[PDB]
Image: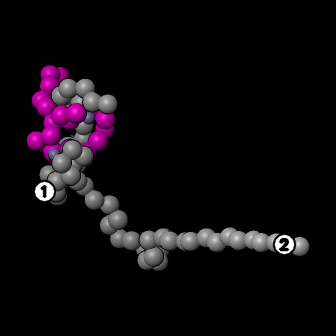
Amino acid sequence: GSSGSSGLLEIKRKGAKRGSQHYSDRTCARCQESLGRLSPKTNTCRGCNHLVCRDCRIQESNGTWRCKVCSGPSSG
Ligand SMILES: [Zn+2]
Ligand SMILES: [Zn+2]
């Protein structure tokens, strides 16, 4: 005769109870800089609707602008 069994799980979550005040940050999407002073609402790339600074974007016509990755060359 013979037999054998096994099995186990590992749970790991944030830890802190359900209550995270200000659990959101605003950092560039190309340089991940501190966009604190800057405005993320307006600093949104119309291309990929992402968050970038006034340094990782390019000025375009029709008062539009896109991120280097967008306005710049193609990227896989
Ligand atoms: Zn973009
Ligand atoms: Zn940037």
Q: Main secondary structure of the magenta part?
A: loop
The colour scheme used here is one colour
Label 2 crowd (10 A; few <14 / some 14-19 / many >=20): few
Disc number placed over residue 37 in the picture, else none: 1
Q: Is residue 65 magenta?
A: yes
- The quarter of the image holding the C terminus is top left
Instruction: Mark 1 and mark 2 in contact? Answer it, CB < 8 Å.
Output: no
Q: Nearer the viewer, residue 41 or 2?
A: 2
Q: Which residues are magenta?
A: 46-69
Q: Give the residue pinned by disc 2.
A: 2
Q: Nearer the viewer, residue 3 or 38?
A: 3
Q: Is residue 32 visible?
A: yes
Give x and y (percent) for residue 22.
Answer: 32, 67
Some atom of ligand 1 lies within 8 Å of the CB belonging to the residue at label 2: no
Give x and y (percent) for residue 31.
Answer: 18, 48
Give x and y (percent) for residue 44.
Answer: 24, 41
- Say left or right for 7 vs 35: right
Q: Secondary structure at mark 1?
A: loop
Q: Secondary structure at mark 2?
A: loop
- Say left or right for 4 vs 7: right
Type of amino acid under label 2: Ser
Disc number placed over residue 29 in the picture, else none: none
Q: Quadrant of residue 43?
A: top left
